[PDB]
Image (cartoon, rainbow, N blue to C red):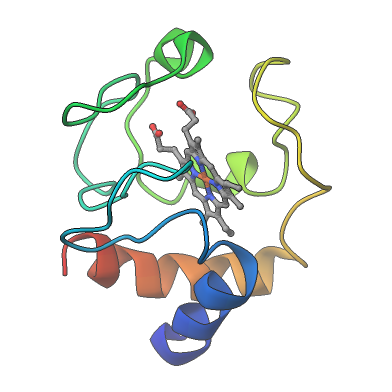
Length: 104
Ligand code: HEC
C-alpha cells in the first residue's frame, strides 16, 4: 500500500473524525494512535462503544479490511456512514499510511 496515497486517502476519507497521531483529541473517531498492536473495545479515557468490545479482536489490517468496507457486517450497531472505501487497492494504501501513522 502506498504510504503517500494512504496519507491523502486518510485525509480524504476520515480526517475530520480520526487523527492516527499524538494529541489527536477526542471528537468522534478515537485518536487511533496505536491501532496496529492493541485489542478492541478499549481506548485511553474515551467514550467507547459496546459493539466494538463485542468484536473482541486485534486490529492489524486483515481485520480493519472488512470494517472499512463493511461497516454494517461485523456487527449491526456501528454508525453506518456509507458503503466503504473505493476498493481493496485504496484500503491497502490506507493501511500503509495507518501502520506508520498510528505508531507515528
Ligand atoms: C467519524 C465521522 C468517523 C469516520 C468518518 C471514520 N471513523 Fe473510524 N471510528 C469512528 C468511531 C467513533 C470509532 C469507534 C467505534 C468502535 O468501533 O468503537 C471508530 C473506529 C474505527 C476503527 C476501530 C478502532 C477501535 O475503535 O477499536 C478503525 C480501524 C477505524 N475506525 C478506521 C477508520 C478509517 C481508516 C476511516 C476512514 C477510511 C474511518 N475510520 C472513518 C468514527 C469514524
